[PDB]
Amino acid sequence: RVSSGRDLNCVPEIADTLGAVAKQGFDFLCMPVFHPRFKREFIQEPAKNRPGPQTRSDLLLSGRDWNTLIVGKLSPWIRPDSKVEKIRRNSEAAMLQELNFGAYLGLPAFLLPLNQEDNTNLARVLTNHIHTGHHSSMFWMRVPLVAPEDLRDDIIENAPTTHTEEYSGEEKTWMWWHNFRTLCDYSKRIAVALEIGADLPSNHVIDRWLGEPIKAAILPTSIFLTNKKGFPVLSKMHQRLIFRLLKLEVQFIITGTNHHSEKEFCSYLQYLEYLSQNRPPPNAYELFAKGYEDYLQSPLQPLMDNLESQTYEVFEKDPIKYSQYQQAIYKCLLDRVPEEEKDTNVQVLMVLGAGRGPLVNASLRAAKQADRRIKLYAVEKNPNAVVTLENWQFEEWGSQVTVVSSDMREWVAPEKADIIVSELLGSFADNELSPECLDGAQHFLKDDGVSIPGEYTSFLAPISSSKLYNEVRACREKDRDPEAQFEMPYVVRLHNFHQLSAPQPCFTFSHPNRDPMIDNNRYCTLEFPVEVNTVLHGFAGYFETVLYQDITLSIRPETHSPGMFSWFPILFPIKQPITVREGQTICVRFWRCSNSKKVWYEWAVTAPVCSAIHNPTGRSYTIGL
Amino acid sequence: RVSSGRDLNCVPEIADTLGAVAKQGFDFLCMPVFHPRFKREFIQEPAKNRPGPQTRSDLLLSGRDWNTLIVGKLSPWIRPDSKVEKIRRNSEAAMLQELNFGAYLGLPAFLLPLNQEDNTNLARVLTNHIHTGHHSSMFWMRVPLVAPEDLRDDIIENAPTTHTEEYSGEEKTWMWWHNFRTLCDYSKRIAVALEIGADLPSNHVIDRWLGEPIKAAILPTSIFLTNKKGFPVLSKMHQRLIFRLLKLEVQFIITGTNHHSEKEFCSYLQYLEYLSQNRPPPNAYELFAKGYEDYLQSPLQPLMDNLESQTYEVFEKDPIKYSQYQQAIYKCLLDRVPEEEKDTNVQVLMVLGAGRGPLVNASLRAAKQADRRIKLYAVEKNPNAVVTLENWQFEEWGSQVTVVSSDMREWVAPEKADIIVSELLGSFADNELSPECLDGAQHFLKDDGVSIPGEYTSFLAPISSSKLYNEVRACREKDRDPEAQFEMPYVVRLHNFHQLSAPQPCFTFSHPNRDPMIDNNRYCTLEFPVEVNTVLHGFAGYFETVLYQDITLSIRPETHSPGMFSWFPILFPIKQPITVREGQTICVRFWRCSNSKKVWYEWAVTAPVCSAIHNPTGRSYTIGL
Amino acid sequence: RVSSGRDLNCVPEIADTLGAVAKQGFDFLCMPVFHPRFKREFIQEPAKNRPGPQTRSDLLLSGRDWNTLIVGKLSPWIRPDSKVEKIRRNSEAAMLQELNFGAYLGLPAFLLPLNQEDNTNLARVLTNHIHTGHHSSMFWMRVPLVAPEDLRDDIIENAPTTHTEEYSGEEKTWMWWHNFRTLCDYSKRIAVALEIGADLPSNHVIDRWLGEPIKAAILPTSIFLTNKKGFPVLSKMHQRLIFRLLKLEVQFIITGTNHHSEKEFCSYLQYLEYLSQNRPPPNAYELFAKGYEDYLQSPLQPLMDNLESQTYEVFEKDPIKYSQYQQAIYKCLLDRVPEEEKDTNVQVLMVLGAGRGPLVNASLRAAKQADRRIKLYAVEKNPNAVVTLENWQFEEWGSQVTVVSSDMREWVAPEKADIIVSELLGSFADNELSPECLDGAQHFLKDDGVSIPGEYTSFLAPISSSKLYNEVRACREKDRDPEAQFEMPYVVRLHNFHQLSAPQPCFTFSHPNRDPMIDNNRYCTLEFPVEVNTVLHGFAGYFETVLYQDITLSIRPETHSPGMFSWFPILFPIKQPITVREGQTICVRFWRCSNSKKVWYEWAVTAPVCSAIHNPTGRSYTIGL
Amino acid sequence: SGRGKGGK
Amino acid sequence: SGRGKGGK
Amino acid sequence: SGRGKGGK
Ligand SMILES: Nc1ncnc2c1ncn2[C@@H]1O/C(=C/[C@@H](N)CC[C@H](N)C(=O)O)[C@@H](O)[C@H]1O
Ligand SMILES: Nc1ncnc2c1ncn2[C@@H]1O/C(=C/[C@@H](N)CC[C@H](N)C(=O)O)[C@@H](O)[C@H]1O
Ligand SMILES: Nc1ncnc2c1ncn2[C@@H]1O/C(=C/[C@@H](N)CC[C@H](N)C(=O)O)[C@@H](O)[C@H]1O
């Protein structure tokens, strides 16, 4: 279950070391490719002409072993940001030499430190190697949660440690990483190897790393506590951080010497396995969404496009959704037909957008449990789904169900309905065009008629995720605007991210709509208080719907319907990341626009800084009518 | 080993039929999605309002079964190219309906016939469905080797069959396919389902299909002969066609009824398995090149780039190449040192571009078997490979070998050489810049010195391959000229192709070069006689090299060194395909160009029609110096 | 000379008004297209059904008059950012109506106000009209230097005016403009109509508008003072602002009623003409650079490319440059040859990169005025210029001059030089590769030899210019990285810009170079103090050179050689604009990089925020060797 | 899943 | 293999 | 002029 590596700075014999490390149960070894003490000269004679091999041969291991079991480490003397010109020049040449050897060997990853504020020249040399040949290898930036200068023992008489809170100051190492990756222009081959110390910083320092591309977590043996039996364990707070890192599926790296001397070495790794086994089992939703974590998808458009058989099959796998619709229809039937009218009053029910028939079946189950009489119409514009419906109608339903192959906006209904039932909702509620569809169907609902759903509301929340920002960035396609990928929403199971403020309501629609000429166009301004230092990358979108009275469905995290997986959140990205300071307000503007052919969203950030208006006139994204 | 399907036009019960077909050993079923006799009306009342389900439900099979076991078939009444306007309109609507149902079901493939010359409207309707939604499904165009009109029995008194040879006329069905795919603009989702008849046409008709995207071969039961035991078998000529199709890894489709009534049905499929098992086993080269068939690769550039450890490891896996170099060095040493000078004469040998040391080892083995004394220098510009060489020098070679980390063009040699040994050859001989490298090294070779290789010659041959043309076409990348992919060579193990004329020599280089100021720039005109009707898509490139006297290496097909897999052929594509008629001449022009920074090739076809000059000034492709 | 318009909000008769305005001497009329009081309803009955024409006919003026003489004005009741939903909706519909009528009429410009902080919805409606049809028209955003709220009379008893300095607060209207144009994503069709008040704000508020696209300056009649004769005049401070605006070639707009009642109306416009006539006449440089103001150009590359005859002709038009070279050679000759050695000592002078011969002529004039003997070699790699040199040598120079058609890095000189003279300098000193060229020529200069120039230094200064940022932005080309235009320098006569900090030295080179193996690669960190609120868009580059001792050339603004126009500054842009607050430090990093084939620059901003490293590995820009 | 299509 | 790199 | 080429 847990992927773990050993970090060594001393490898006297490569084959013997790998064997010992594999026996201990580790999956990989982080090790120096050149002797860490073997300082090399490239410019001055006589040392520049040092003979013999500069390092160990590639012949010592198989190609498979170099490709899968070895993570390279940059030599500790390589200081590209040195104040000394000579060191800076020798370090640039040595860094390029070591990175080129790593690429020669086909190493899956290479470790580089971020151990001071200024790594400008280290970033420049790294960016230059990245734009030179084979683009497969990963660079893991070794950065601590807490800088060595901020965790030093208070033992220097004339230099006391700072006992005052420095909110932004304690977040310093994040700015080391941020500046480095900004310089290297968000290369996807550049990730974080987060190093954990004996004492954890405040939660705000830890949360600063949310949404960051963490590929590895470094655990020094010195951070481990000892139990009554003498075996290495971790503090409750450390365990809480391990659990968070396990959800990100990071590779753990064990560094330092055995400090539990009379208790063997694999014990550190045995403890990580224990924590991994002793974690909460995933729920129905989590087991369903496994594989979709941060996987960007195009939002379905069931109006403009005809959904495929398997899409309808995925919809139907959600037990919660339909049992909620059944409960809403059941209550509505009881409210509309008194017990005394039980055998004479036949309610006309229209399922508008029937798909393969689950809401038709939900309506019939609802009528049986309410002990009421119903007359059903199943309206569906997709002719492929109409095949399934017509086969169901002949084989099972009978005359009680009339299947209609039509767009609900065009259908000349032969009778008026008591109840119209539909499920035309997207992840942002109105994004599949439920308002336009139900507005066109409204004329065949009786004056006292009920629409299920009765109402829906979309919600937005600002988010931070450099991981998702880079994921959207990589969606640049040929023959379109090079920035179009930032002007369109994505359906995504948000995972490695930070929600920056509580979701706030954006747009509301009510059915039936009794505000003449309707006007489904909308304009909303939202002001989000932010209590953290962060970077804004986009807005998470959710929704809630009132099916009937107290019977609802929600994907809003705080009121999420339990076990309901029909909708993942939506993400509205922004083109350029926005720095937000603690105590600032994020002000976002969202518009719902249309013409007679298409509906689209436009959005902009106006505080703390303005962004461009995204998707003007639906230039990058539209929803077909 | 053999992937086979059953073709049926009668499926009374879908579940029962699939079971019977799977029991027989078939992997898939080609079947109608709508009843083949169920003609539908879309325009005129009352028939346009026909009730009930238009077809069978998607619920009859699992999603996995629809995705993997079912190939859809277009209804036989659908005639988009009919002379009758009403049929043409109903057919367009029915074709779109059936293709949309196939996509709804998630079918892996859908069969459409090419059974007449004019399929313009069928192509238009297909192109339109392709540019509408989900782009995964394959379209298999069912086209016969021999048109039904050309294989009809000679039984019509007033309409005799043509007993005269009509060279182009017998190739008619290829033009049906060619026009169709040209209309659909070479979509990669459009492939051939080649139908085989009782009597095979002339070889030229069969060869016309070389280089075509054949995904399936259709075998009617009526083409099978009967053996003494009463079991279905095939004629020797049919078997010869099955073997060719097996190399293309086509899926076989068994159509028609059981004609071997008292011998069961799976017997047809058992025979295909027999032929598949009883085929020639692949040689050392064929087993090595498995997976690389028609796989386009960038030609290696060992001068501009530093090759990776595994690249050198692949080079070293070729036993033939080095044993040839050893034989060439062995003979040279014997010719240069008489037996009487055996113990006094030490020959100075320089391995120029030593990589990880195989030619150094080949030189030492050669000196031992010749019973001669050698002094070796191993020159290598790649510092990563220099690590391997220096570790070999300390551990094994000793003082006899001097490892030099330098470019051979810059090295100030301390002594002159008797023999310079190098392997700087590409798939087109001089494409890795061996002439420029050995020209710069020439000054340190003694006046009577020998260069191994002594000479090399590139060869070109015109080829037809719509498969490869489409493969190059799909290499369009963002931020470059949209046609650059056609102006660069590819290293490719050519497989599904037709060589149109015998390879002819293009460029020759000799070492040492005794034509002052050298001039490695070249211009060659080649005239290729073509005896077939075809389509020109590019030129296959090969080479031959004289290592020493009669010791050679070759990748030219006719003189290919047996078991040598270090080089696959090179392919120079052309932007626009060129129609070539039997008896015409293909005239190609090739240039080898340079400046002090880069070397490149430029090429053009001038007969039967002119092409643009490809890669002018190295705008799409250059070889770094 | 001065282009001026009349602003009216009352036009009873269009033809009569235009005539009166033209008679007064105005070139255009800013006027309402719909009656400014004619509020229209689009949603509610009965007013939405108001009959008759909604405005005046397009037939009232010729197409030429609408295209050239009329600037449209948005109706004052149109409030797209109103707190009232109904006003917001009617305003969006009215704004779209009025903008569409302006485009229907073919108006050259349309005026829209920025009169409050929030214009989010006004920007959204404008962006939407811009992405709808004909893309020619200009939008002039009417924004005041000082907001009406900040210049109101101190006459409200319970609401006193703020008598405290609010540094950023007084710059508020710039942030109104900045946010608006950020929202509209820097459309080039969106410009500023800057409105000037009776009292000017502090210089920092005025300077905030430097580098902004100001197309018009609005002058209310109420800001004009009265002279002893009773005619309208302006304060000295107002005149100082008019002079600055005249250099930007803004169109002046006269708004308000005649306040100089007994002195006619054209008097306001007569005063602007007076100021325009009574301005400092342009110098030799300013007259030369006329037409090149903010015109981006590719920096010349005289090494990689052969300059054209007219390019050399432009070089030769600079009298200052060559008279400086002559003075430097004159002094050098006197320092090297004592008076007593006058007739025996012949100095060997080599002009390295001779072009068409001006430095050869400068050397001969220098030797005549020094009364010393010279032996000249004129070295030139461009064979076209060699034609001019060889014709000069035969006709005029004679045997005293030896013309050499060669690259100075390859030439086998037959004698060593006393002095090497060259002019291989770019706008950033070393950008034409003078260090690499003179390094290769160094071996033929005598041990005590002199190189003219002896030294050169490049300088950088941070700049603000939204005008130039948009100019670089519009340089996106097909078939290249969509952001490459930001990763390359431009030679540009910087005009509409703000220099944010004093130029600081970047890179220095000295000739002859006595630091073995030279290393022309460089890395510089510069920290620029910024005393203003601004936006960083790039770095201006300049240089200084020591020809010999005190004889220098400079384009650094503070030490600019008078009347020397051979070099305009260089501009290094940044991809994303950077907000800088007063008192912050701009930290920039610049690298000079190379391989044996090319030289390039890489640059990054690290404070107040990090930028990406620009041009890594020379991916967008290189200088050929 | 979750109302989305495409991706990889 | 066969003197090539890249592809897929 | 001023050491530049191209533009418009
Ligand atoms: N204007 C329309 N008229 C009829 N059906 C529509 C219309 N717009 C969308 N639909 C269909 O209604 C649909 C609804 C789906 N979002 C839900 C499907 C289904 N009721 C289920 O919950 O499993 C798709 O089947 C669409 O084809
Ligand atoms: N100008 C050059 N100087 C030195 N080595 C070079 C030069 N150009 C290419 N090479 C090297 O020579 C090489 C040759 C290869 N094509 C063959 C490698 C090796 N001899 C083998 O047969 O396994 C690569 O290792 C290159 O790095
Ligand atoms: N390596 C080189 N060898 C010889 N000429 C060169 C070289 N690099 C540049 N040049 C030439 O020297 C030149 C210099 C110009 N920048 C100045 C031209 C001329 N001296 C004038 O001031 O009017 C161009 O004519 C180039 O062709």
Image: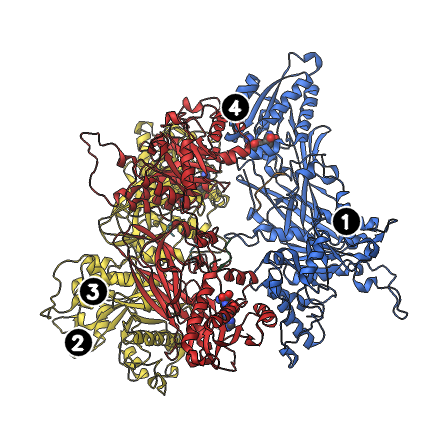
Chain colours: A red, B blue, C yellow, D green, E orange, F cyan
Image spot of residue C498 (x, y percent): 28, 54
Q: Is residue B87 above or below residue C491?
A: below
How far apart in space, not on screen, are marks 4 and 2 (Cα)? 94 Å
Residue denoted by label 2: C259
Q: Are marks 1 and 3 in contact (CB under 8 Å)?
A: no
Q: Are marks 2 and 1 on the same chain?
A: no
- Depth check, mark 1 against mark 3: the one in front is 1
Residue denoted by label 1: B270
Q: Amino acid at mark 2?
A: His
* Left-right relation of C545 to C236: right
Secondary structure of the residue carrying tag 2 is loop
How far apart in space, not on screen, are marks 3 and 4 (Cα)? 76 Å
- Depth check, mark 2 against mark 3: the one in front is 3
Q: What chain letter is assigned to the residue under label 3? A: C
The residue positioned 61% from the left and 23% from the top of the image is: B361
Q: What chain letter is assigned to the residue under label 2? A: C
The residue positioned 52% from the left and 81% from the top of the image is: A412
Q: Quadrant of residue B61?
A: bottom right
Image spot of residue C378 (x, y percent): 44, 38
How far apart in space, not on screen, are marks 1 and 4 (Cα)? 59 Å
Q: Amino acid at mark 3?
A: Val
